[PDB]
Image (cartoon, grey):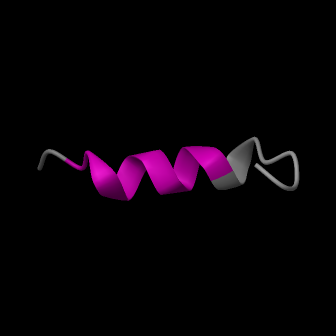
Amino acid sequence: YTNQNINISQERDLQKHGFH
């Protein structure tokens, strides 16, 4: 329904750089 914490992890993986 909401997906706040589940969606932020999926977004970081889609545009990952390396060591944050």
Going by the image, does 15 lie left or right of 1?
A: right
As rendered, which of 20 and 2 lies closer to the eye? 20
Q: Residue at x 53, y 54 (%)?
A: 10
4 in magenta: yes
* Number of numbered discs overlaid on the protein picture: 0
Determine the residue located farthest toward the left in the rendered image: 1
Q: Which residues are magenta?
A: 3-12
Q: Is residue 15 magenta?
A: no
Left or right of residue 5, residue 11 in this image: right
Q: Please tell me which residue lies in front, 3 or 19.
A: 19
Q: Residue 11: x percent and y percent?
A: 57, 44
State the image quarter where residue 13 is shown: bottom right
By secondary structure, the bulk of the magenta-drawn segment is best described as helix
Q: Residue 19, position in %: x, y?
A: 84, 55
- In the rendered image, residue 17, in percent from the top left (x then y), is placed at 86, 45
Seen at 24% across and 50% down, the residue is: 3
Q: Is residue 10 left or right of residue 1?
A: right
Instruction: Identify the residue at horizontal 75%, vertical 41% (top origin).
Output: 15
Q: Is residue 12 found left or right of 6 in the rendered image?
A: right
Residue located at (88% from left, 54% from top): 18
